[PDB]
Image (cartoon, coloured by chain):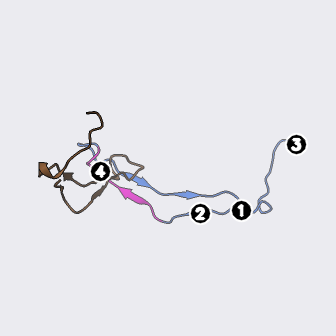
Chain colours: A blue, B brown
């Protein structure tokens, strides 16, 4: 499993959009699916 | 014809209002009309 990420979390705040409120906008961006299909086995409980 | 203007291009980026966007607001200002009415003649195609 290969996770790709950017290791910092961008933070913004704005009295400018809503006037009496502050509205903290924080976001980080991150993603990943499997790189190697032979390296993960699963336990199915059915059969 | 006399053109009056400011020689720049004011850029204001706005992460705040359109929140997942950046929203560059750029505005220069310019005006102008004819200064010497004798120095422009026209070709009318009618009559």
Decide: few, some or many residues near mark 4? Use Cα within 10 Å; few <14, some 14-19, many ≥20.
some
Give the dominant element type of the magenta stretch: helix, strand or loop: loop
The numbered mark, 2 or 4, whose residue comes first in the sequence reads 2
Q: Which residues are magenta?
A: A8-17
Decide: few, some or many residues near mark 2? Use Cα within 10 Å; few <14, some 14-19, many ≥20.
few
Q: Is residue A3 left or right of residue B47?
A: right
- Mark 1 to mark 2: distance in Å? 11 Å
Disc 2 secondary structure class = strand
The numbered mark, 1 or 4, whose residue comes first in the sequence reads 4
- Mark 2 to mark 4: distance in Å? 29 Å
Q: Which mark is residue A4?
A: 2
- Mark 2 to mark 3: distance in Å? 35 Å
Q: Which residue is mark 1?
A: A35
Q: Which mark is residue A14?
A: 4
**Residue most toward the bottom?**
A7
Decide: few, some or many residues near mark 1? Use Cα within 10 Å; few <14, some 14-19, many ≥20.
few
The numbered mark, 2 or 3, whose residue comes first in the sequence reads 2
Q: Which residue is mark 3?
A: A47
Do labels 2 and 4 touch, CB within 8 Å? Answer: no
Disc 4 secondary structure class = loop
- Mark 1 to mark 3: distance in Å? 28 Å
Percent of width and height locating residue A43: 80, 51
Query: Residue under mark 4: which chain is it in?
Result: A
Percent of width and height locating residue B39: 15, 53
Same chain letter for marks 2 and 3: yes
Percent of width and height locating residue B4: 16, 56
Q: Quadrant of residue A38?
A: bottom right
Disc 3 secondary structure class = loop
- Residue A13 magenta: yes
Disc 1 secondary structure class = loop
Camera-nearest label, 1 or 3: 1
């Amino acid at each position: 499993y290969t996770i790709a990420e950017r290791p910092d979390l961008r933070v913004l705040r704005d009295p400018f959009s809503a006037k009496p409120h502050v509205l903290f906008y924080a976001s980080k961006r991150v993603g990943g699916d499997v790189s190697d299909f032979a390296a993960i086995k699963l336990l199915k409980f059915a059969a």
